[PDB]
Image (cartoon, rainbow, N blue to C red; front, side, top):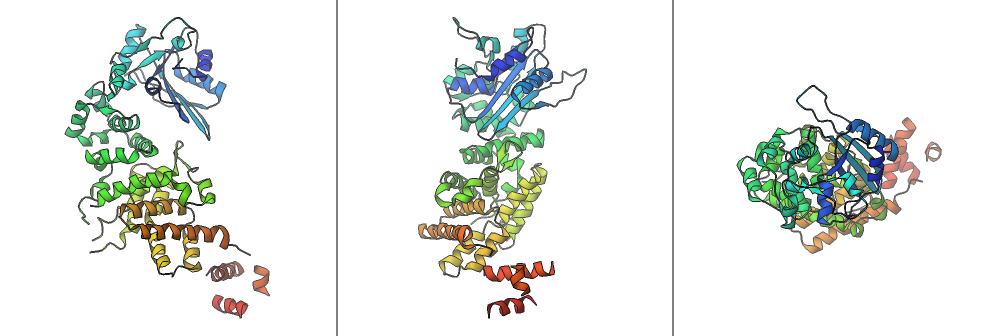
Length: 455
């Protein structure tokens, strides 16, 4: 009843008569927790069938085109997982399929469950048991006793060795703990305390994926703070640790910048214009993530250049862009993604300048047009980041209002004031280049002043 999903039926139709499937990990966990199903559904499976064929035909039934990547060999037993990803804008589906092999089915299932990272993820149920019609409580498999830990609200790794085998999970342990609101056990925290840099063992792609999963949630700032306190964030991103040596506290300012940024993004309807809000957050990166996570990375990286420069900081913020680019290359971020974050960091101080020009009444069509021309793409993100950084810097409420009103002045100037009205009038790319220069003069006796300014 609780464990039911519609597509499971399709699985049962694809699943061979002599082969079985088991619902494992996150889905059963969240289902026991009694959490309402979100817009993202991820279900892990353990099957005795061929995962490739099973997931391929399931993918033929529901769409969600077939995904199989792993190496095959005589041994060591090399896992092959086949996933189905069905993506429509409001809802995303991911079904994982993993091989289950052995002479004793139950012993093999238990054996596989004991290898998993945490007790909450070690709970597995049988597919045929979920589809079972009545007169029984569907049997659950938790040799690690995940249910008991979930009842006590504790997130306990099965064994520390499992964490040392796959270090990236040490990130999950934090994230889930904040995401499902669970308290991690003592042995975990102690293990992280002993050797924080262990996370560097696992592949970089999975690290990036996990960190993006962290940046996805609205509680992200807490998890980031937790990763920074244990030195994990410094191990993954050495540049963040360098924010430590420059004293005004820059690191606290950055964490608070993120924490405030989340609240601002929640309030984004207030400050931002509707035309900006329409296309905001709808830009996909890495196939499961949006530009919002890039905005949060833009909050963490908002000043990464202040430690590099030293009385005042001047040219760093551009340097911030370069550093962000380097990290993006090292962390295997998407090209357009790391370019977006870099561009977001580069201009991070721009709305403050326009604000200062607004408070003095110096802000005019020239500065606005220059702004929107230079960056119109990162404009909303830059606005939210500017407001957040204004909240984190302890700016006066009047000054913050000046920033918001400056932002909305830019937006109002763009949505309505800015209109191109041509080549036939100028003659009354040599003509196109002079048309762009005359356009900048209109965005900042009339015809003669434009013809003279062009030559």
